[PDB]
Length: 176
Length: 176
Ligand SMILES: Nc1ncnc2c1ncn2[C@@H]1O[C@H](COP(=O)(O)CP(=O)(O)OP(=O)(O)O)[C@@H](O)[C@H]1O
Ligand SMILES: Nc1ncnc2c1ncn2[C@@H]1O[C@H](COP(=O)(O)CP(=O)(O)OP(=O)(O)O)[C@@H](O)[C@H]1O
Ligand SMILES: [Mn+2]
Ligand SMILES: [Mn+2]
Image (cartoon, rainbow over all chains, first blue to last red; front, top):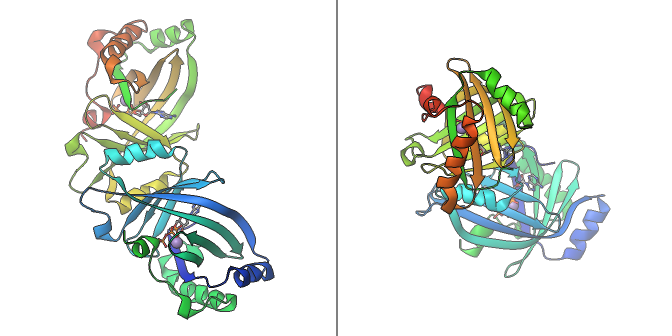
């Protein structure tokens, strides 16, 4: 379900979890992972070299699913690739050797559902509240156009409205 | 078997493969991989940033074992860390995003054996000949001299003499 170099996404603040969950129930959404605590360590060079290029690099641990990912996001906000990793500390030390060191951490509760080709990701962050992201994976930049708007069609059928859209990343929201 | 941020290693030209193999049987070596094709893609930044720090970074595929490794050697002597990865192409693209691109590729045939704490590799490189590496990984910097001396003793035991020692790396031997 996670194949491709691009994650076409639309993110929204969620005003009621009840109606969101009813729609998930309505549309026969498949649960992939539910209520995982996700801890994301963001790494950068000592002069913020990656952020100066619109790139984020993260080591993510998700519990209790046990999933560990190395993620490189950017440049831009569709480009995203990740790799499952066995050992977060081994990868972190290897990256430190290359000059990347922890810069900050973002924690969240996350659930991920599927409806056909769409991912619906439901997040809760301590300060900030509830969010949902509609996303579609692709490997072909030559098809990015259709997908977004389609995340918009799906989001339109889903009760996630423009007035609630949130274009900022979590690092942007948190001042990192 | 492959635990540590330090790797003590001695590489030898092999003048007599028959003696080496006969000693592998006599010493009850266990084969970890036999006659694998190993393709190593060396990666660096456009300005050779890693080489300038005596760091090498490799994505290795070994067939038919199916082992895939991301390896960061250095900076300088005796430092090496590796992680298993599921997909070379995927990590390669991730590293390309960070600015590291294929600089050159080395191919070889390699068998890897264990005798107690020691690793013995038997390599053949088409333009160059037959080599064997004797190696021990550790996290402890205080024993590196002892371990290297143990490797040299161990090697003599396979008919690999002090005078067949090869301090140059394959990348150096191949003009990279
Ligand atoms: N279990 C899994 N296996 C493989 N890849 C996965 C995965 N779970 C997620 N991914 C991939 O890794 C990417 C991670 O990106 P996101 O989770 O969207 C960052 P985020 O925390 O939402 O922050 P942002 O809004 O601040 O950018 C996903 O787009 C997806 O492609
Ligand atoms: N299956 C595995 N799991 C984890 N680590 C491994 C592994 N196989 C090998 N490694 C580690 O990664 C290192 C890779 O380095 P080498 O294979 O020595 C590069 P090389 O091709 O020999 O050229 P060189 O001449 O520069 O040494 C190994 O020495 C080993 O310590
Ligand atoms: Mn996201
Ligand atoms: Mn070697």
